[PDB]
Length: 460
Image (cartoon, rainbow, N blue to C red; front, side, top):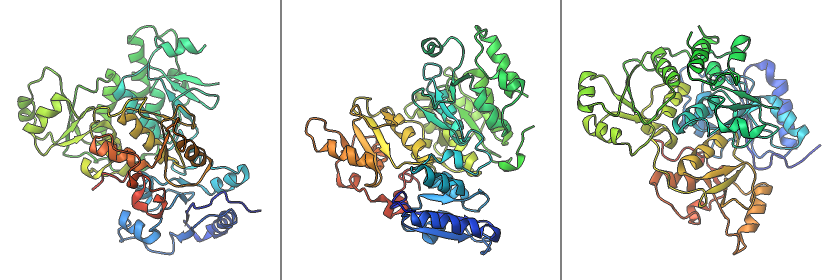
């Protein structure tokens, strides 16, 4: 049979071994018959990538200049996986995605189909209660859920598998009463041990209404993650942070066991950690510990960071997100070569009313990235396009969402604005409410170049 399911979408099929040529041909036939635009096949085994720099430029020239929308692979073992998955934010999905995508006749979510073995939560739709955690915790838990392959949502549905609460005291458990209430160690455990959560430890992570105090909470955290991981092989640079010493801002006020976790994460990768206090004298802290070369803070406008930048003018200025990005890439990387979301957060630019936005054709890590951007711009995002929405953000002109929202924008009353993701990124980069109707933000043909992939604006 035929269809237009894949129209204007480019695919890259990776063939790990000659024994895969049948399923590669089979998947490419499925892709062509359902109207893929460009549908390339590339044989990993037939070219000694040993000793050739398979970096971003290499990938861009070899497989470009148009963007690759999906990389089809049953393994992540190829030398440009990190380039594709963590930098350019292109989904990497098993052949099984193409078959199911055809039978279901829709763009299936990619998470479930990632071949990364670290993506232990690929199948979870997790809702993190904002009534339970402060900003810096919410961010950190969101980052690690994303690094573990799960999906974040912003309301509870029948598709929600897990709800993160800090304690029974939180007003989300009251106002609700088939999903599960869990403590954040359910996330942290999978991250730290790189294996599923089973046994008593599985039950230690579920909400217990008899946890009325704080000492019990501490106790359950210490047993689950206090004290030998599986899949040792997965993140093998155990010296990632060697000779680096991080100063931790007080403006992340973590739950103390969560600070322990973050401290042990750094230390297990051979780095050092000094926590800062509001009542520290900072000239003395950086003279006592002269090896301190990094600052970890929540907010760009903190006074602690201001004095620190004057004392230590070449210090690396990052947020907690930047730590885990370095871990994903397995290389220490100055913030200036990472992404906009890895710097200490700007003051909130927009309000909900000015910025309540829907999006379309953003898949996998791109979806997480557009939501993080809206968040730190100070607005809201939604999975479905309604009239509440103030903007629709689009990358192309394909699909029923752009069609409907493009119509509503012709009406003088509604006044909804269709524009591309580079408006988000440029607003944040410049820290200014730019006009989404400028011509550079009305380019709906970004798929013609891989450099216009969301998340590229701001790297060096």
